[PDB]
Image (cartoon, rainbow over all chains, first blue to last red; front, side, top):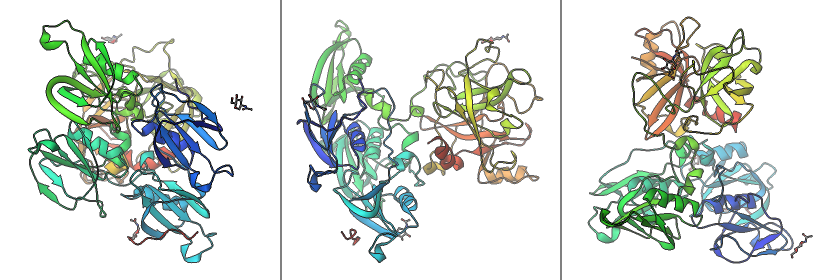
Length: 596
Length: 8
């Protein structure tokens, strides 16, 4: 029951949790969605009927009935959060606000050629939440073209005022555009001593770090594990920051872990989605309900289906003697976390999966199935698609990868002498070519996007996008794959897979059942040595030492997520010599601008 | 950090 629609001139009476300041009601709704308690909100827009102090007031509310009394008021905009909704959600707001000054701690001031450039700085910076930028037209001269960066405890501005000839906007780290490097490397037996800006109780360091990530002020963190000596401090997740933006010192200690915010790589990593169960762990919180459940799995589904429930502990029928109906405790707290974490009273705890819809769908797990080297099989590579040509007669043309609901990502060289999209057929989730028949269902390609600069495969820009006529219902058979995040350029991928039907040209011949081969990456420079006749750009990556087709995916698995590191472009020829691929990372800005 | 707010 998503009421996505905002409510004009309406105020929701009472139930306030807190008050923040947002540029729009529309952003208020996002803030409400992402706060652990908020079901609904009331925004106060700029207007005579209200004093300047209360404009941009965004009031986060909760109700046990899940709603509140509506009273009309001028300038009041009110909504419900998206927790209640099936549709995916994003925290990424690209709005520039004209004549708006969003106040905060101003930690840096400089000259910028424009709002956009000011914003790329806000985004590329470790501390930046939102920026304000003074235009030329700005009367006071030495202030002209100053782009000043700010941060707050909450990530939202302490106040908002109208100041003409100025533009404010938010960091785009959550639009997946930041060039800031993510440090995924986690330090066991380590602690950090710097400003502690908040603290939660976490079941492990993974959740700790996830929590660090979506917390606006948290740059790095320390976790005091269950095995920590001081009892009071166990499972305590400490969220830290510093003026440099780095840990002042690495102190050595046992049973504590440290790490960093992943805010940059936010889109390729599970963040709000905690799918593990925690056994003989009980999560202390406020009790919402207690119900009969057959298992901790249905326990969780009850949690997820209960909108106020943030977490649960399931208590199983006792010690295998008892009838198998357990007790499901639906819990909540003030942040979305446990107040206390207790080990050894034999409950099974986890979180609400209602959160997961905030994650990018390319982060969801893939059922284990069977790992057979010889052949691929159902659901194994949900992103890979086969790209078919009608002319002369219908046959496999290329490989492609689903990077979107509406999008395939593939090679440009695949479209050589293709006169229109109208001849293209994209099939999804196909194991066998034999499997395709006249009745087989497929996606029509609405549009082919080839790189402005593309000329030839061995020239660099071999990449293309397909926009589909019709969006994909994701299924264990057909899913997206994540694009490498720019913050990850230094990641070392040790597990990589070329998939496809084996078409690098009509000769060679083709393949029926989808083929899969794990392949080592090879360094550019080492690659440059095997290819003398040709150059190898920073926009190309190699591998080998090759069952894939043209436009086919190079899928690297990192931290339990699949990334599309490269697209098969020209490798001449199975030999030894590695395939040369396009470097997807290097095209991120490009893909994003094209897909939005 | 000294940084000053834009004049009204």
